[PDB]
Image (cartoon, rainbow, N blue to C red):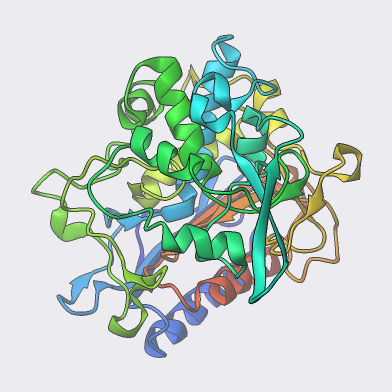
Amino acid sequence: AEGPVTATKPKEAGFTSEGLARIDAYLKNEIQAKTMPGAVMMIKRNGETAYFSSFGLRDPDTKEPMTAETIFRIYSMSKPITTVAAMMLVEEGKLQLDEPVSKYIPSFANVKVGVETKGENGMALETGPVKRAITIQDLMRHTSGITYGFVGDGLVKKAYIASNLFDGDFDNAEFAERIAKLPLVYQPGTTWDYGHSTDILGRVVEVVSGKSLYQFEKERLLDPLGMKDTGFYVTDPAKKSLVAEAMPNDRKIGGSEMFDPRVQKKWEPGGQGMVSTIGDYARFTQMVLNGGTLDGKRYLSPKTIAYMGSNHIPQASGIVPGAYYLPGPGVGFGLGFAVRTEAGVTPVEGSVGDLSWGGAGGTVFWIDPKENLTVVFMAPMVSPRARVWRTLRNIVYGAFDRLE
């Protein structure tokens, strides 16, 4: 419990009051069940705030309250931000989608692809050349052969884990070199597989701009949008106590405790590193919903936004799903967004063309152009995150009084 953060206009937003009350009841029940210590959620539709409420605690140990100003590790919700940054360089003609990553990070020129095969002592890796160079587009839509060691299983993934990629205090340049030493899981430009591509893309942004990923983003996006609590580390002493923490039994991601964003380090990974607030991220998603503009400032053209929100892995692309196609049936993938392709099929409510992604620490968003809708939700949690996110989709769409 705690409730509304601001005034709302649910009827002009095309919802019922009864419908939106289902969100309150669901979230209060989940907090009671210890799914999360607390939660904050914002719904924007037809240019109005339909819903903006805070419940429970931001940290179950300190018992500090959940607030709009609470700062979350957003993990993979870093990726749309990184991709937008890269597309700004594309619009300026400083970066191209068909270019090889090796143009900017030469160590990717001679990466090899690992294939599992039987040896004398069980399965082992054979390695061979890439048929095509990894492209910038490949990074943006996760068809590069670059993977995550901790997602699923496989010999290349085991090699990632064995290389201890996250040891020490290193920067985006050093991380890119670590990744380039590993075999690829698939031939570049053939297969969708989620991974460290966006961390590599972040380094490309640095090479092109001559700035750190954060400084580039700060100047071009975060400052002008008013995302004043978005970055990679919480360095302001006044804001360190605002970091959301999960229930004690649900604080591990990738087998390790969540990183402490209050202690600044060199790494600024565009795939996983960011911290933000619900208000900051909603400004970002409203800007995207608006076709690249907010409060009279343009960040990307509406054509660029439409292009990012298009399916870049339909059958016509030649791309196939890998062993771990996270979006599932009826959902494709664009430049940093899952893109719904079927009205039914996917087992959650939504609209063809809706755009979404989430973070391993419990944060999620979606953007629904058809319904003039964006939703951001943040609660610190890991294990139950997917079922909560899916349920929230069903409740939000179930609360509609009309279609746009």
